[PDB]
Amino acid sequence: MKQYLELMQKVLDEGTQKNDRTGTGTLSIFGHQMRFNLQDGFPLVTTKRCHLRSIIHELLWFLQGDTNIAYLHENNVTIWDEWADENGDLGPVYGKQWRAWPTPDGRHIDQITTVLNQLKNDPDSRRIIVSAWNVGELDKMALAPCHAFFQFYVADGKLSCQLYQRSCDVFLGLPFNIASYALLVHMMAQQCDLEVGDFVWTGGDTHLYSNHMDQTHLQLSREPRPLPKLIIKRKPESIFDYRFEDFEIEGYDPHPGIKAPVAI
Amino acid sequence: MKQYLELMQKVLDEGTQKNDRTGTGTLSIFGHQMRFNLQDGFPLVTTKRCHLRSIIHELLWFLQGDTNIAYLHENNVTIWDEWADENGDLGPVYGKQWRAWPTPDGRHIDQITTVLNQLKNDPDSRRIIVSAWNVGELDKMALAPCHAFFQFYVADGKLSCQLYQRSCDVFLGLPFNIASYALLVHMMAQQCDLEVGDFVWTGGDTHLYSNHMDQTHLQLSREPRPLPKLIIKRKPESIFDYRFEDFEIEGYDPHPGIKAPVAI
Image (cartoon, rainbow over all chains, first blue to last red; front, side, top):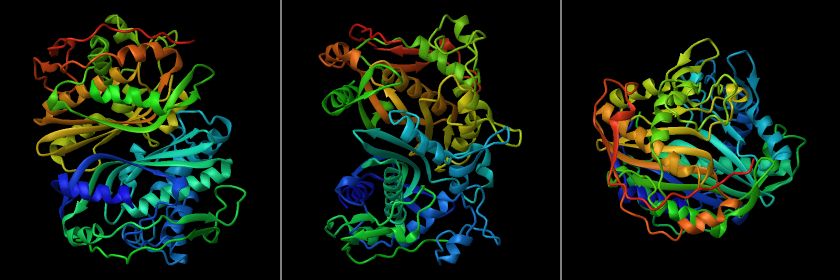
């Protein structure tokens, strides 16, 4: 899609050479913002075919407060294997912070139920936020949260959401992360009887890996295709009741998928 | 300044009518990003005279982990009186989270010393972040943090910083908040032997109060003047050693200050 393709070209055009953790060099820009009107269609990159099944499974896993790989495995979703230990444990990552933020005095905060309450009881609030950046549990996580902070906003019966992404692999990570949060806004909106608004993406260190140049140039050649339409075939009793089958993406005609390897 | 004036006009041009906590209506836009190259001069609004002394005093107060009004009072700085209790206590706000984030197991995390370590030992890190959004202490704070999350970034010997502001009063709050963080980048940079880079401002609910329309129109009439130059007359032994006298702003020729009242 247009905004995505503009970002890629920008990193090429003005990114500085910056190496990552003992490895691959990257082209980096810092601070960037994109806006997707979810009313214009589901923001799934069309200039390269992307598979939604791992995204859906991972989101539903975040919502259950699950921090172990078991559920993803039952569904043959393997995107977190890289980080899990021999027990399939990832540490207090996303799921754990969203559903059970540990307090100094022994409580566990359900940030997403809190948010749902605010969206229904105080829609004009400027504090409808969920954070996965728990400073006290950072050392125990398999990896610090990439998408660390997100805020919801209601205006004219429309639910918007802004995500702060501290680090971003534009080619491999971003397409996957935009869809994941877009999908979450739709679920949130359906649950609160609100129309979908905007999904604003805000990133910090936004980069392209040096060994992805051929692929980015290949993708930059393609012309974006019309955005698909996301359809929820059911209306669960709560946000923790969604099933993989509930979602259907209609009208998705993408260019062929592109593969990008990684150093180790 | 230009970016600031563009924001004001934008809120006027496309902001929706949105009321705040049991009160004044506002014009609101959600998600906005501005960039200031600190090498081009200190970002202090010139189209309306602003006073830096309360800013400096407040920043130095944040750095000391102080959460009580006493220090500001000794200096006749009264911007936090509104929130303090009869004891001058504000609760675990900014200062407390920056210098002593409480963990579930009894530790207190010095986020700013952590950051300083990372800037000197691992400058290419994508995790150089300080968060004041401690979910477990939110109920105890006089008010939830407005400027809740900020990330540092190093590239080409230049220190950049991105701030996420959940809520923003464009006329009254923003000018004060841009200068405060710009000043902090300079101190951080000086301490780490780095040049200043960019200060990226990212906001969520960015608004203008309805009863500020005359003032915004007055300010929107003025032509921005050259940005002043920030000079630190000393190089303290640590970031916790700065004194009010250390800072001097040179070449500041602003238009007359404008006052904006508030409902109660």
